[PDB]
């Protein structure tokens, strides 16, 4: 078996290998990449997402989110307080202000230490889930707005045509902005391109050990667990690498830099934080191997977890019992 220790693998496709997206994902999996739950892909040197990032300041962040923490330094929840709209130019200026800017630090490790020590004492503002794309329309390779759709994948594999669309989302981050422990909707893949700015650190649990993380989460967030059988779908729970280690949860970490892609694999729990002002673009996608994960994906129906219009059809076709119950 390839990659039995479930290490995060890093790939350097040639420009020829970068043409066929589906084929390269399949290649990565043939090398065991999916066992980690996360892979890094460094594009060939000949490739670029767009010419420049010079004219992005007038993009609007309609609903910036202030991420307010509760709990302990290594075990906390965050809730998102809505703030007034601001442009990306205004957001960048805010990110670089004394209140919000990245502190002096020696290296990524020092910054990671500072993050877990001090995150709960601040409330950074995140511009998340902004529908849009920063890929040039002429970028033909790994353009996250030109991928085959999940709806077409389902149709190709299962022969059923369904409604729905899926399009990319932009994320504008600043120091300490945080993404909570989660898998994707319907345990889909995701792909994430860091367009510009400071790095993003990722933590990931191998899919074969995802239930170990769930069990720990139930212990660490007992009220949340009682409220919903799939409360990690709420995207509110953070657990530090120190606490994971103390509880013997298998995981890995890696830092993504500007110009790099990350792929998360079905049922790969992940969490992380931004180092400073940056912009990422991400989208969910599927492969034939995803279908069985989609069938088995847990669902939130306590009401908390927000779900796209397109996720309806996935549940309807792949989990008809759960769909029928959700109706009545
Ligand atoms: O940027 N890419 O991905 C490229 C650039 C040139 C090529 O000839 C190619 O096959 C891929
Ligand atoms: O703020 N809360 O609700 C919290 C904070 C930490 C926890 O471990 C928790 O179960 C709930
Ligand atoms: O709050 N902490 O630091 C904690 C809480 C629970 C744990 O099991 C742990 O190893 C650390
Ligand atoms: O455990 N699962 O994954 C299940 C259990 C029942 C279902 O009806 C389902 O669609 C998935
Ligand atoms: O970048 C973020 O804030 C969160 N991204 C993801 O969870 C992802 O790409 O799957
Ligand atoms: Ni994700
Ligand atoms: Zn719920």
Image (cartoon, rainbow, N blue to C red):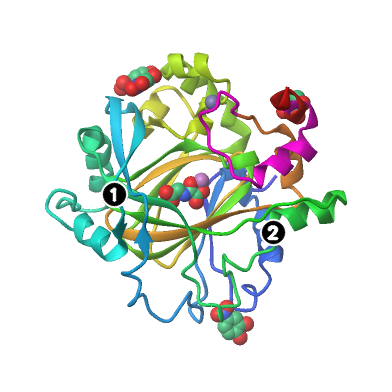
Q: Is residue 296 above or below residue 143?
A: above
Q: Position of residue 168 (x, y in %)?
A: 54, 59
Query: Could you tell whether 147 is left or right of 216 in the image?
Result: right
Q: What residue does disc 1 label?
A: 84
Q: Quadrant of ligand 4?
A: top right
Is 314 magenta? The answer is yes
Q: Residue 146, position in %: x, y?
A: 62, 68
Q: Residue at x 48, y 28 (%)?
A: 249
Question: Viewer-nearest of labels 1 and 2?
Answer: 1
Report which residue position mark 2 lands on.
Answer: 149
Q: In this view of the protein, which residue sits in the foreground, 5 or 244?
A: 244
For the residue labelled by badge 2, is the local secondary structure a helix, a strand or a loop? loop
Q: Which mark is residue 49?
A: none
Which residue lies at the image location 44% right of the left edge and 14% below the top edge? 223
Magenta span = 300-322
Question: Label 1's element?
Answer: loop
> Residue 254: in sight, yes or no?
no
Question: How crowded is the residue under tag 2: few (<14 C-alpha within 10 Å), some, or many (20+)?
Answer: some
Give whichever of discs 1 and 2 has the lower sequence position.
1
- Res 98 visible: yes
Whether the magenta-drawn stretch holds residue 168 is answered as no
Q: Position of residue 278 (x, y in %)?
A: 33, 60
Residue 305 horizontal/vertical position (percent):
53, 33
Name the image quarter holding the N terminus: top right
């Amino acid at each position: 078996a390839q990659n039995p220790n479930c290490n995060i693998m890093i790939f350097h496709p040639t420009k020829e290998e970068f043409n066929d997206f589906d084929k390269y994902i399949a290649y990565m999996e043939s090398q065991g990449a999916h066992r980690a739950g996360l892979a890094k892909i460094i594009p060939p040197k000949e490739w670029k997402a767009r010419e420049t990032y010079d004219n992005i300041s007038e993009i609007l962040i309609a609903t910036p989110l202030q991420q307010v923490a509760s709990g302990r330094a290594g075990v906390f929840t965050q809730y998102h307080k809505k703030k007034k709209a601001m442009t990306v130019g205004e957001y960048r200026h805010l990110a670089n202000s004394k209140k919000y800017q990245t502190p002096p630090h020696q290296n990524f490790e020092d910054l990671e230490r500072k993050y877990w020590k001090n995150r709960i004492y601040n409330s950074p503002i995140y511009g998340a889930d902004i529908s849009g794309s920063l890929f040039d329309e002429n970028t033909k390779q790994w353009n996250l707005g030109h991928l085959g759709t999940i709806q077409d994948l389902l149709e190709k594999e299962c022969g059923v045509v369904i409604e729905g669309v899926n399009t990319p989302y932009l994320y504008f981050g600043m120091w300490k902005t945080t993404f909570a422990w989660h898998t994707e909707d319907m345990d889909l893949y995701s792909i994430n391109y860091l367009h510009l700015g400071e790095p993003k650190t990722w933590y990931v649990v191998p899919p074969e050990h995802g239930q170990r993380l769930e069990r720990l989460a139930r212990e660490l967030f007992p009220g949340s667990s009682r409220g919903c059988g799939a409360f990690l779908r709420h995207k509110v729970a953070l657990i530090s690498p120190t606490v994971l280690k103390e509880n013997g949860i298998p995981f890995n970490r890696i830092t993504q830099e500007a110009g790099e892609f990350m792929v998360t694999f079905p049922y790969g729990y992940h969490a992380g934080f931004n180092h400073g002002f940056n912009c990422a673009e991400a989208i969910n996608f599927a492969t034939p191997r995803w279908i069985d994960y989609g069938k088995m994906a847990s669902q939130c129906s306590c009401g908390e977890a927000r779900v796209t219009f397109s996720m309806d059809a996935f549940v309807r076709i792949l989990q008809p019992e759960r769909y029928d119950l959700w109706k009545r």
